[PDB]
Image (spheres, coloured by chain):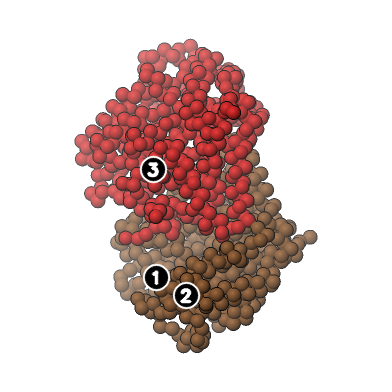
Chain colours: A brown, B red
Amino acid sequence: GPLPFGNSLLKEFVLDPAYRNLNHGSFGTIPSAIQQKLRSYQTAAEARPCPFLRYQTPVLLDESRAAVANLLKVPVETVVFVANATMGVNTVLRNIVWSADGKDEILYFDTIFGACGKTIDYVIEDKRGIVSSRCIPLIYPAEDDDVVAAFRDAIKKSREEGKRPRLAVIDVVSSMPGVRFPFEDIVKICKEEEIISCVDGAQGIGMVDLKITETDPDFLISNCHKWLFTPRGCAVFYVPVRNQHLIRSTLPTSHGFVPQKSAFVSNFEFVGTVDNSPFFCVKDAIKWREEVLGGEERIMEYMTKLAREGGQKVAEILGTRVLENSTGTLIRCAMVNIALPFVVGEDPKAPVKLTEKEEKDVEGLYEIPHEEANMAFKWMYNVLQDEFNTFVPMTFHRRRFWARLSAQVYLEMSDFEWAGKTLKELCERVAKGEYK
Amino acid sequence: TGPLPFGNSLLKEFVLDPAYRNLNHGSFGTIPSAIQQKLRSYQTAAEARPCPFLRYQTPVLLDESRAAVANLLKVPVETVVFVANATMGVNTVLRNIVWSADGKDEILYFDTIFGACGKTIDYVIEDKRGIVSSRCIPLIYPAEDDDVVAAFRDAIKKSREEGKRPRLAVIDVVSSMPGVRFPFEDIVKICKEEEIISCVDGAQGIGMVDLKITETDPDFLISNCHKWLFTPRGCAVFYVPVRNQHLIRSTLPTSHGFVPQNKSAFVSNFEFVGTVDNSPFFCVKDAIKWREEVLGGEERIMEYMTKLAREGGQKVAEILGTRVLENSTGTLIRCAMVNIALPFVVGEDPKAPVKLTEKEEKDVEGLYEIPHEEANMAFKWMYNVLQDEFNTFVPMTFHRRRFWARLSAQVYLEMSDFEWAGKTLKELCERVAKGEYK
């Protein structure tokens, strides 16, 4: 039968027993059964290179394409594997041909992943101004209605400047901070307004239900290596059949390109020589998660609940609060943010008008001068690795540090309590000016 | 004591199937057992400490592999980075070039260019909406070095005669099919004289021939470490002199290092371009070390494989009674791969007839002729036979009505392997003369 969750499940993984993994959402990790699968695929590749790599690669790709589309509840003709989420997002933006009038505009939110945000910048530079972009600022904790309204005002405002809102990139779950984004509402608005919905669901498969069919996005990308126990360097790229014709070239351009099984699926089979073993392990990771663990829903059910209750314990230990809106829809994933018990001094260049609640929440804590914010930020990162042998990413949002913790099926309440007590003393030492 | 002798005794150090004969190392390469173990050690370290290792040890390990490969190529370390493969870095060059506003820029390339790279030109023309064009330069092999230089000098001229401007030339170090050493020293020099960006595709390069980077001084060069440098698949070194690093505006794909308009920003840009297993990149310093301490260094490795390619190639040509692909100057087989014609002719195609050299018509009289339509049928048949029954693999170039089989020598091969290749290809070719491919 299935195995119980918690620290006993560390038996199945290959983490350092001295190292606490509180940040699975960044790079992921794989259990011992999947690494051996990974290395098994390599031995076959090095045993007879041309026979295996030329003819067994498409068979092993389609076995994982079938398993992942199955689990996503979508046709197999619509899923394909790319290197990673940054690669997939780049594949969408680099392939779109923009209107000849030059009125097209890319809409995005300021919680966009750094790599994604800078891809929009370069594409605008590369196409030399035939497409532009407008940034939608977000204040967190964000109410879902405020996010969708800020998107509607961006659509309305863009048209008042003579611009055409052409494409919108929507997170499933944002990176920093790790919050569930109301992507269903934003994608639906994109359809009504005829906007290409480029759903960046890197924090997606294996953690939250993507609801691909009912949402019907134009493009979706998601990192299997982030929450599906898939070896590093694997993202599932979803393109409906109606849109596969605009993905004209892969990244990079390879043999499958035709100058002007489907041709769309075949073009991604060989895109330059790479170790494709992480792709082949998708079918095993899915089968391992269903047989060894209780299944996909049981995995997500535990991680989300542990993120709530575990995050609330870190907040009690710190005397602060988790990051959540009035409807409790931000912590609908496996990650949770907790505010740290201090505050940064005001930036005279870009001062943030603090909200009355955010100011009473500052309640006379220790204040780090803004000139020392980056210095203390580096210190907390190094100390968490060198002294506590863990790693906690922190979002600097409105002169506060929001530490993001990632729950997993091999963690339990004791880990988040250790995380709370660790962060507690770490901030006590930040309060004493130890970062200098 | 001393280094290890070459030949089949060296297979103890590799992880090939003993029932499989790897006569085609040039396609995907392979790694020794010591390098595979290093690949898994980097893999083990990443899973033990995802964030601490991948965030902070990746800079260090990339820099050790950058210094190792830069010293091997005798190149400043500030001018080398690592990309995914040869196809990836050729795209990196062609997609960052800002073409001139009027639209006369054209990309020069030869028709023996690698298939992915030529189509990369076709897509860049499409994505840039016709402001850049291409001009294919046909080549006939056996090609003389003077004739290649002549075709390039006359293609530059026909361009400007049409009011066009040669902007960039895709130049091979060693071409894929047929596996042949290309006179890149002269074509790169002519690109400097004619103000043409030299984009060198040296995928067949590192670990096999002397790239002579400092001397020929190219604008951009790529080379597959995983092809001939015993590096795990998914690795290729990207050489750009710092005079041209500003031209690479964004990596492929675009990531944190891009900036809109100690370690240089160019070098920093290629460290994190998306979540990937970087174990192949880290092994570059381990492969170069292994090749030095165990095999005796690049120059002993390279010249053995080039010597074996000639002698073993003429054995296959002798066993089959044909010939090898070589020019009058003996400059085509200046690498580790050799092309030997198979003993039969393809019927002429009325859709594009091959008017052949007098000497070319004398080399095929008496040979069994296969009709042109059945050519692709027997081509697919020979591939399946050499794998399912002879348990090997040999790629074949179709060029002017004769198949040239491309063999790949390597430190773990010797003369008995090429004798087996010739013996295997006669059994194969005698069976296509009897029409077995039906």
Q: Is residue B395 left or right of residue B184?
A: right
- In whole angstroms, how far apart are the C-alphas of marks 3 and 1? 41 Å
Circle 2 residue = A397
State whether residue B312 is above or below residue A102.
Answer: above
State whether residue B352 is above or below residue A436.
Answer: above
In terms of sequence position, does the residue under pointer 1 or pointer 2 come before the other? 1
**Mark 2 Cα within 10 Å, few/some/many (few <14, many 20+)?**
few
The residue at the far right in this view is A1
Circle 1 residue = A135
**Mark 3 Cα within 10 Å, few/some/many (few <14, many 20+)?**
some
Q: Residue B307 at what x, y percent from top left?
A: 49, 21
- In whole angstroms, how far apart are the C-alphas of marks 3 and 2? 42 Å
Residue A306: in sight, yes or no? no
**Residue type at numbered disc 2:** His
Q: Residue A359 at what x, y percent from top left?
A: 47, 86
**Residue type at numbered disc 3:** Pro
Q: Residue A59 at what x, y percent from top left?
A: 61, 44
Residue B7: in sight, yes or no? yes
Q: Is residue B172 left or right of residue A27?
A: left
The mark lying in front, picked from 1 and 2, is: 2
Q: Is residue B389 left or right of residue A382?
A: right
Circle 3 residue = B76
State whether residue B144 is above or below residue B232.
Answer: above
